[PDB]
Image (cartoon, coloured by chain):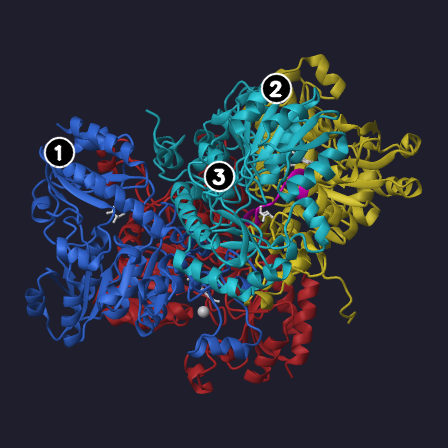
Chain colours: A yellow, B cyan, C red, D blue
Amino acid sequence: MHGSNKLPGFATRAIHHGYDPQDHGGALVPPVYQTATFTFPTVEYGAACFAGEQAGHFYSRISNPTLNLLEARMASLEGGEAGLALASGMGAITSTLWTLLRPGDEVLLGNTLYGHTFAFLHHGIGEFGVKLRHVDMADLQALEAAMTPATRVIYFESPANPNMHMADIAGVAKIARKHGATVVVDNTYCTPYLQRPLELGADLVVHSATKYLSGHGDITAGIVVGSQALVDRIRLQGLKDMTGAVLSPHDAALLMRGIKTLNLRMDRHCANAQVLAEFLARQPQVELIHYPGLASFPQYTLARQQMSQPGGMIAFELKGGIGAGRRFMNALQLFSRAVSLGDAESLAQHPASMTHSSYTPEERAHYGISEGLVRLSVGLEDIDDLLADVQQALKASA
Amino acid sequence: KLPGFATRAIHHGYDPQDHGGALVPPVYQTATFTFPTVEYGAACFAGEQAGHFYSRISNPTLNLLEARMASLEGGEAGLALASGMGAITSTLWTLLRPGDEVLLGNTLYGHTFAFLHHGIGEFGVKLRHVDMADLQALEAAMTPATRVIYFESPANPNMHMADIAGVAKIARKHGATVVVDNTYCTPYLQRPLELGADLVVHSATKYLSGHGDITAGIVVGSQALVDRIRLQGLKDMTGAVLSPHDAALLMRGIKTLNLRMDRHCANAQVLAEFLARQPQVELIHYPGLASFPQYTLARQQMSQPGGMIAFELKGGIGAGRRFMNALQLFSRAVSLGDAESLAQHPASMTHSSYTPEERAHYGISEGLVRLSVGLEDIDDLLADVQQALKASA
Amino acid sequence: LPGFATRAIHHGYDPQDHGGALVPPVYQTATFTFPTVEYGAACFAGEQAGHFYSRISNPTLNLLEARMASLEGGEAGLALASGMGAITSTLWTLLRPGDEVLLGNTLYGHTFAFLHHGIGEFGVKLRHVDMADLQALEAAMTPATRVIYFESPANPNMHMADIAGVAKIARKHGATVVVDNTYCTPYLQRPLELGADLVVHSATKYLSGHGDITAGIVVGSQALVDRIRLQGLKDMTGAVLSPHDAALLMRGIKTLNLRMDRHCANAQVLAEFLARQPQVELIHYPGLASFPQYTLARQQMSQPGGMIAFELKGGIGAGRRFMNALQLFSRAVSLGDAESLAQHPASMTHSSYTPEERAHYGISEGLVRLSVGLEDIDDLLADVQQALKASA
Amino acid sequence: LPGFATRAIHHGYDPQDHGGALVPPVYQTATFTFPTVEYGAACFAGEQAGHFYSRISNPTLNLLEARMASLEGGEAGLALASGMGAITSTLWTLLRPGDEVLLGNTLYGHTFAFLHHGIGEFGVKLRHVDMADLQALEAAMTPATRVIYFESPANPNMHMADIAGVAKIARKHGATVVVDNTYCTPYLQRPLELGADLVVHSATKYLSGHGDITAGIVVGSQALVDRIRLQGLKDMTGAVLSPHDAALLMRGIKTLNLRMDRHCANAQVLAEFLARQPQVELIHYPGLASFPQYTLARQQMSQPGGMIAFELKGGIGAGRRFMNALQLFSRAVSLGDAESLAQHPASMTHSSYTPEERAHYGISEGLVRLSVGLEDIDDLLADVQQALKASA
Ligand SMILES: Cc1ncc(COP(=O)(O)O)c(CN[C@@H](CCS)C(=O)O)c1O
Ligand SMILES: C/C=C(/N=C/c1c(COP(=O)(O)O)cnc(C)c1O)C(=O)O
Ligand SMILES: N[C@@H](CCS)C(=O)O
Ligand SMILES: N[C@@H](CCS)C(=O)O
Ligand SMILES: [S]
């Protein structure tokens, strides 16, 4: 009944948006433009592609048809005007912030960040005269209080890596509308399938597409989505001049392949993580567990409000300290010991004996890392196998 | 002895016996790497165990490419990145902070110029352009703030050369780091590290790939400097990660680098001889011509005069446009170092929205045409240039 | 012991054997070298765990083969450049002049062409029988019957064979049973667990799932697969799979369970919808209680599949108009892609024929085949609804 | 006509037809869709003028085919999954029971195996004759002779056939001449210009040049190639080339002239060196004045090639010591890689064999075959020199 102005469903757009086989000789899958350069029919047509007249292509670092399809598709999924594809999540983050900030500007930051994002801010751009301040983005009164006339960007992850701390994106956007700041949200953990910060009033979203968007752990990639004006600026300054973080057309095509199953994969990641999280909460050895789908989650209602499903990531604390975590990790036979997330393969990290092993018990405390803490990226394996693996690894941790 | 260049370009750093006898190295198209124990994992993030954890930091396919490029440039260490701009920005973001000065060659690749003036230069880094062939002017331009000297040699548009050894001697007195963009020559024709440069950068998109189908960058230098560029510039400040797939294609291209460069040079030498005596041509810049102003310096630094030609047509902008439009084998495109021959005329292409005085300011003649001479049969390339020249009347 | 999804992701691979790489490195190499001539000697002799040449064997292909064997519950796998590569390599190996092959009544067109215009012109005898009629199959057996070959479900009406029933007859008489399991995949049906000797796939379809590679798979005993590798593939077809494409196929397989669940859920809704429409004369979908072999389908397949066949009341003209009207479904041969596909044989693959020729070959004038994809079912229903209106 | 290097880079592609892309986009798609069923029908009926399914045809494959056709001076090209795919698809199409095929005296092992253990077991008669002996060839011609098939140069001698002389005989009797041109490539030898009807290649070797793909090519008349495509490939082998690998093959072809120049230059230096060494019993290299067919080779081949065969004094033991001493050459099968390769069949491929059967075949106990690569000749000379000392 209801006519042709209806938005196609998410799965339909993830598979089809922006591509009609009739435009490429009937190829069902778009051909891969693995070409660095594009030629011009005449010297004037070439002039126009550099002088902003002619729609077209000239050099793959600036723009490429395979990348453009990926970009338009991601834009559709996030409810944004425009997309940009980059060589990594760090490429997306750095290209964005290098574009938007200059000496004397302030950036307001979420209290916890991905480690390399933190390092970029504190040891990179923050050493070039950009002022940094961290604020708890879940405390809208504190955020309001931290706004200064120099605040140019508000940047955060929700949920945040690795503690799953959340912010009310719409609440932040409302503050930013009143004051003027540009809001940038790292939406890696949720993907557009679970949360769409642009639809809640954020200006820009960034992704490590290396994670769930790819889904298969075989590419490194970044995405930015936002307004045409901001994404164009990031493309033509951040990417073109300031980072050179160009995505391979081969990898862009793999990313698109992954996006075709994004809904199905996220459904399974979330279903598996919910079962594991409920199981873990009932085990003798587990002292504490943080999963957005449990009512014990400190920001349960904000998670329910913003996220359509509670995600594939679990954090928990074992009784018995670092010795328990070490024995837990070494006992794992199906979960892999590794960094990253959003792969088909289930992954685990025990930061006390892995990423933060060089520190002592005191230093891990002020960062906020328990000696029995472990982060799980719950994969796509049979839940009974994952339960069996965690169950036997808990037995070895005792 | 040291194996020869062609041998190293094919073999360096890889023994098939280490990868199940595979003649061609397997492609590590993986974002993450797992650990057998948390102890093994711990050591990699601190950096005691020589393994892998994450492909943005390091990956075995990229490592082979890096080692091989280091061998060809005669440097300690290599780094592979998503583009030439990824190489340049990762390098300069690592080496420079507000109040530092970078001394620059008088002309640079457009986006390098843009990065410098509208990017890092807007974050408090000072820029000064100097003629890198004028050693007296370079010495006089040095200040206590000078931390990097950066240039291409040869440089667009007129293939102007720097005296690399002369620059390094000056830099050494002031502690400064010399960075050379060696894209045009490749390590097969010129090795700036052997002339005293500290670091070399490449757009591997060009000749190193050779086939126009990847975008990639390379940095080669000392272990200490390359480690910092990896762990700061790449890891944190650009994220310009090269795909293992593209790294494998780049290695495939490098296996024929000597043969391709020989042919690019042989073809350009013929085209330069032809163009230098055509009526339509006012000036020609080709390092292999006896009349090239820096003929002697060029021959000290470069083993062959390269695949690039720039020339100026007497009829100015109109002649340039007509020459370009008449080409049927040469393609109208930016880029260089492909099997396919390419041509551009900046006054009617890249720098077209500008006026004549803005182009002369930037150092771009109205009739300036640049050719990337490809690998096609020279008789076909000659016929194309000949008929284009007639059309330019 | 581990679950299907677990095995589809992990079986046969330990990252610690390959520098900790989570994803296996791709062995895109034609040849392999030897540390000594005698290490090389043993590889060609066949008593040395190694590699020499990717047409014979390659580690990327070997992982794919082992994983596919696991999923089908078989001993050994072989990867080939196409479904036809799998079928031809298999039958060229197993048959010689004077042998008889018993065939399902309806086969994929190029399988039919291979049998009748290829191997059948080299002295191999062919006979077609209804594999659902176990009495008729038994009556058709001779001592010269070497191979029984069929698809289940088969084109055009999704006609099924009782695989265990056929296998019993094969064991009694001494024939080798080869089942094309392309439509079901090992996720829905495992013919080797029902007594078949070999299964073949067009991995181009559901196993890949994404329409970007052409590939074939054979699974069966080590004895049979070794012969097919070393004769059919090595000497008689050269249908070698690219390691690049084998890697992509493994990527596809990692989501096979999830994709098939969605294909089947979508197809069930669409079939139930089609069954209620005035334009539709008849429908063949294994998940409808009306399906003639519904009981056998529920017994042999764990889900009813992603494929629908139906007949439009208005015949060839209605078929043409229906197909031409589709905006979301694509007009294409092939199946098992994320994208929904449709074909109407009377106006596409078999258009030059007369109606009577098509009836002889078993294709109705109004027969449309749908490969139901992974799009939102509401979008697919809307597309089919408007196209049915346009079919009049 | 543009020159060979120009055509190897550009033939059949204008960037303006694919959005200005300097490098053609890779059509990694298994299927193609139709705007209407009528358009789709037209594809399956008899015309082409478009695309349907990548096993039949694909734009990436089509470009490779057209370019190879241009380089060989043929009407039409076909790309396949391997050299064996090329050979089998060709011979399965051209031969039926009762036909005879005349073969060169020695063949590539798997070609030999296909002929004798494959197609020869389906009622096709085989007969080996010296393809340099035109009187002997004329004598062997019967009314059933449908195909003449050979390599030139052929292992292990680098024995040359008189291609124009064979073709004259074939045209009188109405036989099709198929030449395996793998060793020379179209850059060195064009058998179609000497009167061959079809050429086949293992594009795995020199055409690729970089050891990273397996692929085959057929080039010949439109009428013959259309048959091989639509019968041999489509129905009888399914040896479909990946578009990814076809793109890599085109990448390799762009440097074919340069690579072959260097392979040939290096091989000549090593052959001249080997000729003057006391360990070497005899040497087969076409560029030595002492080569028995030196004149014929120069008439057919523009350069003497990158392959050397030679015999060591010391037989099998000396071969083993030579091979195991190599530090830059790799012990491997295959040829035409950037990397220099060596093999000693007595102790590698034909090692399980006893020295008795080897004798009446071409396989001497001392026979070593070198695929001379692109490395610095001084390094290759040094490696060969030290291995010869170790052989004693
Ligand atoms: C929320 C978020 N934002 C950015 C990144 C960096 O993306 P990348 O540059 O593609 O690796 C990531 C990567 N996270 C990995 C990094 C593995 S080294 C992890 O912590 O497990 C991320 O999770
Ligand atoms: C266009 C192709 C279709 N079918 C193919 C097919 C093959 C042959 O598989 P390759 O194409 O050679 O991988 C084998 N076995 C079955 C049950 C098949 O459906 C089609 O129907 O639409
Ligand atoms: N250096 C080349 C390609 C980059 S756009 C050029 O300027 O034409
Ligand atoms: N003609 C090749 C075969 C590779 S298996 C060789 O003789 O080595
Ligand atoms: S088909």
- Both marks 1 and 2 on one chain: no
Task: Please tell me in which quadrant of the rendered image residue B141 appears.
Answer: top right
Q: Nearer the viewer, mark 3 or mark 2?
A: 3
The reply to whether residue D187 is in sight is yes
In this rendering, the answer to whether B29 lies above or below D81 is above
In this rendering, the answer to whether B289 lies above or below B2 is below
Asked whether, in this view, residue A182 is left or right of residue D327, the answer is right
Asked whether, in this view, residue D258 is left or right of residue A288, the answer is left
Q: CA distance from mark 3 to mark 1?
A: 40 Å
**Mark 2 sits on what residue?**
A353
Q: Nearer the viewer, residue B360 or D8?
A: B360
Q: Nearer the viewer, residue C199 or A71?
A: A71
Q: Chain of mark 1?
A: D
**Mark 1 sits on what residue?**
D277
Q: Residue D44 — which label?
A: none
In magenta stretch: residue A34: no
Give the amino acid at mark 2: Ser
User: Residue C188: image x %, image y %?
Assistant: 51, 55
- Please name the residue shown 18% across and 62% down the image: D120
Q: Chain of mark 3?
A: B
Q: Which residues are magenta?
A: A240-251
In this rendering, the answer to whether B35 lies above or below B217 is above
- Please name the residue shown 51% across and 62% down the image: B389
Q: Nearer the viewer, residue B215 or A251?
A: B215
Q: Residue B185 — which label?
A: 3
Q: Residues within 10 Å of mark 2 (few under 14, many from 20)?
A: many
Q: CA distance from mark 3 to mark 2?
A: 48 Å
Give the amino acid at mark 3: Cys
